[PDB]
Length: 49
Length: 44
Image 1 (cartoon, chains in turn blue, brown):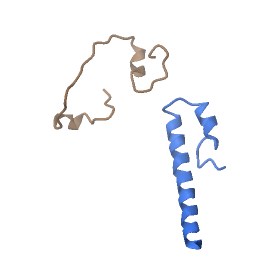
Image 2 (image 1 turned 180 degrees about the horizontal axis):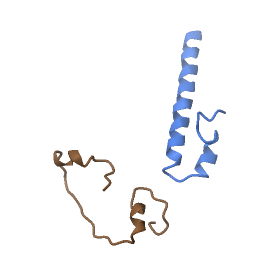
Image 3 (image 1 turned 90 degrees about the horizontal axis):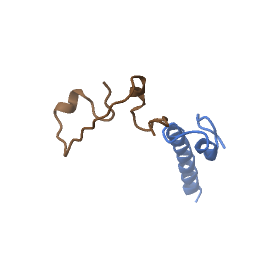
Image 4 (image 1 turned 120 degrees about the horizontal axis):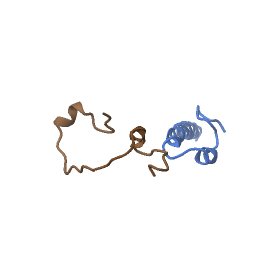
């Protein structure tokens, strides 16, 4: 539920308020942040297993 | 001018497959709307 420095934390709100060249950078920031979170969760799960 | 993707100084070295040039006459202040993904409805 965090925005990771983007203008909003909801992807549908990004795609309903920007065109296809100003929303790309915000989408990139969401991709990077959520990728980091998922990778961290996978690593903790591996050690606990 | 402006170059989007290839540096103009290093353009002299690399080789290309085919180059295409276009004839195009447009108003004076509209020249800044000829760019990838521009918001201009007239440009659209």
